[PDB]
Image 1: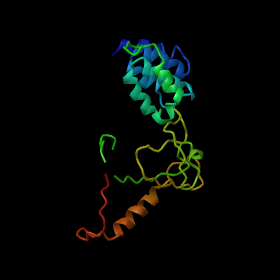
Image 2: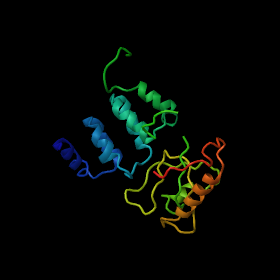
Image 3: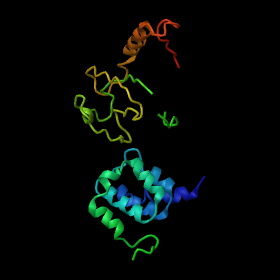
Image 4: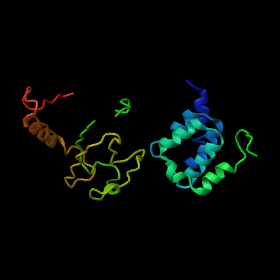
Length: 101
Length: 97
């Protein structure tokens, strides 16, 4: 009922890649439904390190709606934030602007 | 119980061989981290995560479903035979939903 859904689903299956390759498209497209099903499949392979890396990308792109889904994935904020990881959050240039510089 | 969204005992009869990744949970009172992912199509199937109490009767059959029915009747029977401390309804009643 949503050619929107079907295009991006066939662009995912048609991407045919691992999930951390996929998320970096679906966060960019901001479509929360399709990363919740066609990328958060019940058994889709989630290699370590790159879910940490794309959680770092989810924070900096202001994708707060995908932040809470990656909490439900189980990215614990104790294990996620290293010293250098929060240093990367402070030293980034994406998203909106600020007065910090 | 997810739509509960608040504060809860849920007992659960199954066999251990039917549990997905049984080898994940080997360890006695040990806190084995069960990541709540299953295979998309798997023989052994994951116990629902937010259910708490489990039985998991390993009868030596890996996989094979149906090793908890009589034991379900046994538990249900002697808890109904157990005199409830209210003693107004005799033994703790059982409702067959």
